Length: 160
Length: 164
Ligand SMILES: O=c1ccn([C@H]2C[C@H](O)[C@@H](COP(=O)(O)NP(=O)(O)OP(=O)(O)O)O2)c(=O)[nH]1
Ligand SMILES: O=c1ccn([C@H]2C[C@H](O)[C@@H](COP(=O)(O)NP(=O)(O)OP(=O)(O)O)O2)c(=O)[nH]1
Ligand SMILES: [Mg+2]
Ligand SMILES: [Mg+2]
Ligand SMILES: [Mg+2]
Ligand SMILES: [Mg+2]
Image (spheres, rainbow over the protein chains, first blue to last red):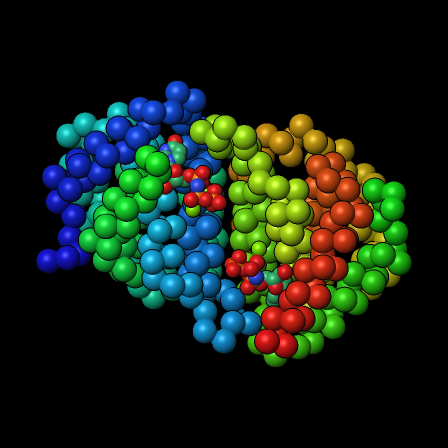
């Protein structure tokens, strides 16, 4: 069952993020939104689907998951900063369950980056959507469990 | 060594890039365009204008210039792959000379990244424009000379990659 997300897991992740962000008095929503986008590209660079010049493209899994965990962190951070109640959690699991286009072949296509950019400059981009994106990448390319594991490791390192 | 770019310097850069890209039989325009965008973000990440949580934000200058050089390389690559004649060179220097918005305060504002993204998703984005962007960053935040220096170093290293 290593590739499903429960409401308890999501709430624990939000709490872990909140306790870290509590240490950062400059915490700023505009910056965290920019940070999400930059981390997304850092992650996309580890995937290397556009790097036709590599003999063996793709950085190591742990490196890919570490970068994916940085996206989650800002996604969780934006969620907490905006306020993320039960109704928001409900809508997240409904959006996740109803997402049919963010699958493996789509996410492996280097051109997906343009679609993502379009969503990233849209000022209506929601905190729910940002989380759906990162969790669907985890579900389809990795597992949710591996993302959560990598996130917990990274957050411990971030605390030091 | 003047923070200016001449037509001879630009033509040398294009020739350096062509000779490297000649070694890459999978050379692909869509991939190079994607690569330009990715390297732009790798470079923006070294600037750290959005990273309010850092005691001392901004990676070292050599790191920042190295990443800036990777953008130049794909910009030069896209130029050569599309064809870059005299008329293209003429129009580049006119665009560069006529660019008044891409200055230091604008480029230091984290929010510029959204403007850049909009330009990057536009399929009408030109090879000239991509070069204007990277050379204005060099001019305003660094010097053109430092970019060229960093690009030449990086291309030597890149030749050694394909060597082994
Ligand atoms: O407000 C914040 C800021 C940072 N962080 C954490 C999340 C993420 O794991 C990490 C990202 O911070 P940096 O971008 O500064 N370090 P990174 O490991 O990404 O290296 P680089 O900056 O070289 O890409 O810090 C937060 O959780 N909240
Ligand atoms: O067609 C090409 C391919 C690569 N290059 C050069 C430009 C740039 O300096 C470098 C980019 O390739 P990589 O992304 O593999 N090197 P980097 O260490 O920057 O990548 P990463 O940080 O993702 O490991 O190789 C070209 O000039 N033309
Ligand atoms: Mg980072
Ligand atoms: Mg990162
Ligand atoms: Mg790179
Ligand atoms: Mg690079």
